[PDB]
Image 1 (cartoon, rainbow over the protein chains, first blue to last red):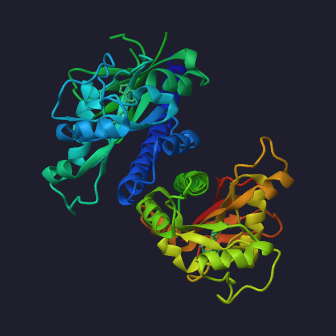
Image 2 (cartoon, rainbow over the protein chains, first blue to last red; image 1 turned 180 degrees about the vertical axis):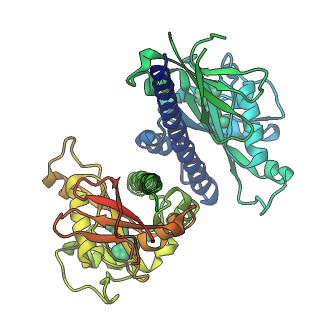
Length: 263
Length: 266
Ligand SMILES: C/C(=C\CNc1ncnc2[nH]cnc12)CO
Ligand SMILES: C/C(=C\CNc1ncnc2[nH]cnc12)CO
């Protein structure tokens, strides 16, 4: 103690706040660029007739703009397909809609969200029905009903098994009315532009290399349910902490960063 | 009056100025990055795709719908490189003639031109104008293509609005650009130029005027690329001569340097 204790607190606050700012900013930049991609698919795939976007073009553009989406492992576009359209859709694409868990031909469902365009980094998503995973399905529904960006809870991503969160933006047909109801949004839905925030790897890359990292313990929690906080980043451990604010841009979810010293 | 109160007065000026500088720098950075994406969009969807997916109508729609991604820009446009040998061909295909910026008159013979072929509707008056026919624009085009990176002009009064602003340009290259290109190779491989108008006078005023304490403070931004010839980029004025603060700005072009100066009104 004691003047040194005060300085120690001031360092913790500064360190934590800066990390939180860095993470919030990189998230925001990624979300904004994903929004632009949703707009691109709408403009080029739906407003233009015939469509003037395809897998080759989507892959090239997304590869070349990967720098615009720093915390994302990849982006993809899933198209809305209702069951009566499935035969026609599968014949057009020359593949069958598959389940996420086993890659098996999808059983009949009322509707599906198969990935038709993908960044090569997530090429394994192609033809998978994004509604066949619960976190993804919930995201898709809330995206299309709200008309805005949505985030999942943290969960382990396909292929890598890295802990992350999925971001989804809805893409609508031009038949969407102005000031639409939710019912109108659903009817006008074309598909879903998604991005995978690979927190486990890419947030570790962001924060783990920073000076002072060995002196502090950093966690990011999804606190959407205050009684059931979910680890998004950091270890599973349950005196002096500091809470730094995070806002990842989906009002349905809440997050915070907590930092502590080791000793 | 108080000496103690004066220290706090300076502390507040520093904080207010530094915050405004950060905001300006960050918003410009966001705009530069989204202009970079547009240059990639033109390369991928107009040049690489056979046939092109971008006509004027498509460019206008996409850029209108994404205007929010580019906060300090009044408009974006794409100018294609046209060498004189090709001019008659280009004009016949487009069904219009390349015009000068100063009078919208048919361009005289020049070695090359940079006519705008795609434009956000906000800068629709740029269509068919040779961007090499304005000196600030011409210098920007050359440095963009030679360096391969984003470039900014000195402050000048923009077309139509006459607002004081700066122009941002990214080069677009042909697929023939070699890896690790020389400058000579970059010039030979140039397709055109994706430009954006930073309307500093209107849009920086809009940004600053909404902030709490705006009436208490005077904010000026200077282009200090030439130390002995500072150029006003933003600002007018009745200001407190006894105290000022300088805040750092980095707008992303190593060829240019800038700073912000804030003072109290009184
Ligand atoms: C294409 C869409 C979402 C992307 N979701 C995923 N993207 C990448 N990896 C994953 N693993 C589990 N889900 C994902 C549409 O919302
Ligand atoms: C299209 C290009 C630049 C855009 N330049 C301008 N864009 C809009 N207003 C202006 N006034 C003078 N120059 C401009 C290419 O570098």
